[PDB]
């Protein structure tokens, strides 16, 4: 259900359902996207819908995602935020590269 | 040692330790800052420095502190609407809560 799509410099996770670990397929996608990213810092935006449960889910998904990225690049520089969207009804994570 | 500093426009809580809540005195400071805010919405940004190892714990601590802070604000100002945001950046040096109006 949760969907991962990416281009050269942007990876977008669109969450669906309950708090989940990443599937084996999602782990591969995130790993495949990071393979060429050794020299990139990462700007991560956790975006949740507008109105505590949703906020908590955004924190927990941010934790999972940090852990996932850190498995590949332990010394990765991350800046990560959590914010409500004006109106999306979607929870998502956007990763942008900043090349170093 | 949790510290509160403010101007008319902005109040910043700098947290010490792992305590989630405030002294009686810091509660009064917050209440005094809110007194001319009855005609305002509020924005809170929880700022969470990055722990090398135990970032899950630090991150959950900021979540919990924001629960308490919103609780304390609404004690004073029951109908206020709060926009909550979180930032955990590499450059973040202190655990703090920034409060602004609108």
Image: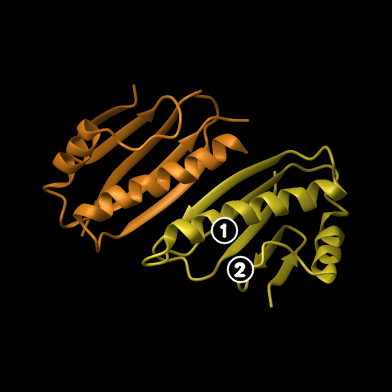
Chain colours: A orange, B yellow
| Chain under disc 2 | B
Disc number at residue A64?
Answer: none
Image point 27% across, 37% down: which residue?
A11
Q: Position of residue B62 (x, y in %)?
A: 57, 56
For residue A9, say whether it is visible.
yes
Q: Chain of mark 1?
A: B
In this figure, what is the number of numbered marks?
Answer: 2
Location of mark 2 (residue)? B18
The N terminus of chain B appears in which quarter of the rendering? bottom right
Of B18 and A40, the residue lying toward us: B18
Whole-number angstrom distance, CA of label 1 to CA of label 2:
8 Å
**Does dot 1 land on a helix, a strand or a loop?**
helix
Dot label at residue B61: 1
Q: Residue at point 39% right, 63% down?
A: B90
Residue A97 located left or right of residue B26: left
Residue for point 50% across, 56% down:
B59
Q: Is residue B58 above or below residue A88?
A: below
**Where in the figure is residue B87, as x and y percent of width and height?**
49, 54
């Amino acid at each position: 259900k949760t969907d991962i799509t990416s281009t050269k410099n942007e990876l977008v996770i669109t969450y669906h359902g309950r708090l989940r670990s990443f599937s084996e397929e999602d782990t591969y996608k995130i790993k495949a996207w990071l393979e060429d990213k050794i020299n990139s810092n990462l700007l991560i935006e956790m975006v949740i819908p507008q109105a505590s449960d949703s906020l908590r889910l955004g924190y927990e998904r941010g934790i999972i995602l940090m852990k996932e990225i850190k498995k590949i690049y332990p010394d990765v520089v991350i800046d990560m935020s959590v914010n409500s969207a004006a109106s999306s009804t979607t929870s998502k994570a956007i990763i942008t590269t900043i090349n170093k």
